[PDB]
Image (spheres, rainbow, N blue to C red):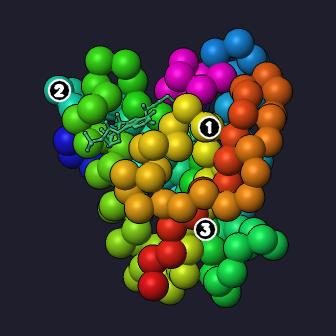
């Protein structure tokens, strides 16, 4: 897998295909993409963008750490899963975040992906909550200090 920087606009197709296929494309244009210091990473394989991840500074009231970042739009295309594409994006992001002096990376994880974040060393906090139309979620975080 080759990890490369990508632009916000480059994430919309895979966000739409994988995460929000039953919603208008506008639902994939996350307002958080326009928050200060937002960045995006792409995983490329065989000449195709096959994994995406987006990060921006956001301090969660129920997590402790002076500087925190949120992960949004984590997705790998069917056919290209189980190749460490997603893990490679998260590890590369952790280097960028550690260099920026971030203390923590968090995500409102789909529960169906909780085991992925667990394998990457994330812990769960709090309770499962539902967010229609995209289902049960759980706050997960990884301290990177
Ligand atoms: C709010 C959010 O952004 S959370 C949304 C997460 N995305 C989704 O749910 C969309 C659909 N799923 C996906 O896109 C992918 O399955 C992802 C992003 C969760 C994982 O991407 P991949 O590129 O396949 O991950 P990668 O290959 O790095 O997997 C790392 C490890 O986690 C495991 N893993 C991957 N997905 C899952 C899962 N859904 N549940 C449990 N374990 C998982 C892999 O088996 C691997 O384990 P191993 O090292 O023991 O073999």
Residue in view at x 21 percent, y 27 percent:
47
Q: Quadrant of ligand 1?
A: top left
Residue 34 in view, yes or no = no
- Camera-near label (2 vs 3) is 3
Disc 2 + disc 1, Cβ < 8 Å: no
Picture quadrant of residue 130: top right
Is the residue at mark 1 in contact range of ligand 1, meaning its CB lies under 8 Å from it? yes
Asked whether, in this view, residue 67 is left or right of residue 133, the answer is left
Residue 18 in view, yes or no = yes
Residue 132's place in the image compared with 38, above or below, is above
- The alpha-carbon separation of the residues under discs 2 and 3 comes to 30 Å
If the image is split into quadrants, where does the C terminus sit?
Answer: bottom left
Residue 32 point in image, percent of width and height: 72, 53
Upstream in the sequence, badge 2 or badge 1?
2
Disc 3 + disc 1, Cβ < 8 Å: no
Residue 46's label in the rendered image is 2
Q: Which residue is mark 1?
A: 110
Q: Report crowding for label 1: few under 14, some 14 to 19, many 20 or more residues within 10 A (C-alpha).
A: some
Upstream in the sequence, badge 3 or badge 1?
3
Residue 101's place in the image compared with 143, above or below, is below
Residue 139 point in image, percent of width and height: 67, 54
Q: Who is closer to the viewer here, 104 or 49?
A: 104
Is the residue at mark 3 in contact range of ligand 1, meaning its CB lies under 8 Å from it? no
The reply to whether the magenta stretch includes residue 127 is no
Residue in view at x 45 percent, y 77 percent:
144
Residue 17's label in the rendered image is none
Q: Which residues are magenta?
A: 13-20
Residue 112's place in the image compared with 78, above or below, is below
Q: Secondary structure at mark 3?
A: strand
Q: Which residue is mark 3?
A: 69
């Amino acid at each position: 897998i080759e990890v490369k920087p990508i632009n916000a606009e480059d994430t919309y197709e895979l966000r739409h295909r994988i995460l929000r296929p039953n919603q208008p494309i506008e639902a994939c244009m996350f307002e958080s993409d326009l928050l200060r210091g937002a960045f995006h990473l792409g995983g490329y394989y065989g000449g195709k963008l096959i994994s995406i991840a987006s990060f921006h500074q956001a301090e969660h009231s129920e997590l402790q750490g002076q500087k925190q970042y949120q992960l949004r739009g984590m997705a790998t295309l069917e056919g290209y899963r189980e190749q460490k594409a997603g893990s490679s994006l998260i590890k590369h992001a952790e280097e960028i975040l550690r260099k920026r002096g971030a203390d923590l990376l968090w995500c409102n994880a789909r529960t169906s992906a909780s085991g992925y974040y667990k394998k990457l060393g994330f812990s769960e906090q709090g309770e499962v909550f539902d967010t229609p139309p995209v289902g049960p979620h759980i706050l997960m975080y990884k301290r990177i200090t």
